[PDB]
Amino acid sequence: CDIHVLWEWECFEKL
Amino acid sequence: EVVKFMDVYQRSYCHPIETLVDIFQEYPDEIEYIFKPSCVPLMRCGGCCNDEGLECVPTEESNITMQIMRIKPHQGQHIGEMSFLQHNKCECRPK
Amino acid sequence: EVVKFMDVYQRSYCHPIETLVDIFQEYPDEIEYIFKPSCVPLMRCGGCCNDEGLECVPTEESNITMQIMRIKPHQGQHIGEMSFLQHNKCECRPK
Ligand SMILES: [N]
Image (cartoon, rainbow over all chains, first blue to last red):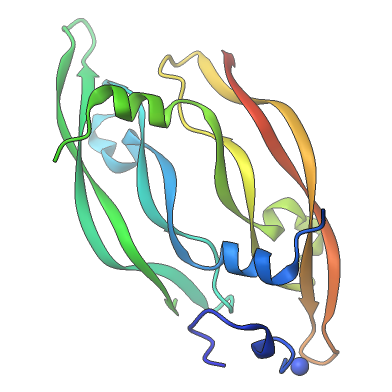
């Protein structure tokens, strides 16, 4: 996900 | 009882939040005077971004005018309008 | 169009207010870690007492525990519990 915008949870389980 | 991760993350993420600001921060020329109240509630960008390389900054601003008392040593009380900057929208941008 | 004195005065007077706090301010020993979020929302004393010599202090506290992620670009992420102090009551007290 774009680092500049508020994330959903999948943005974090793609870390 | 434990706050869930996504709740924390969403609540702290960069946004305009009511912040109690000391009038002298905004009006540093006036430190030898006394204001009542001495601090004012403003909407200001706060919280955090997804990366320590980004910062939470205003992308829309406006003025708010408030009725504030000011007194200089040995003078009488004045009261009047004082204007302060508010943050209406915030975004995370490179530092 | 102008916020009235008393409204400013009440709204800025010493009370507990939602404050966005960087985790390293609370856990400075932990700067070897990248936390996500990097800041947390906490009820904390803020505002003014309007009477230098009077200060806005916590008079009651509790803890709150939150799920925070700790990451390492090499390693996989962990999610852990971190506890923080909250201010439940604030009062204007002689410095
Ligand atoms: N990841």
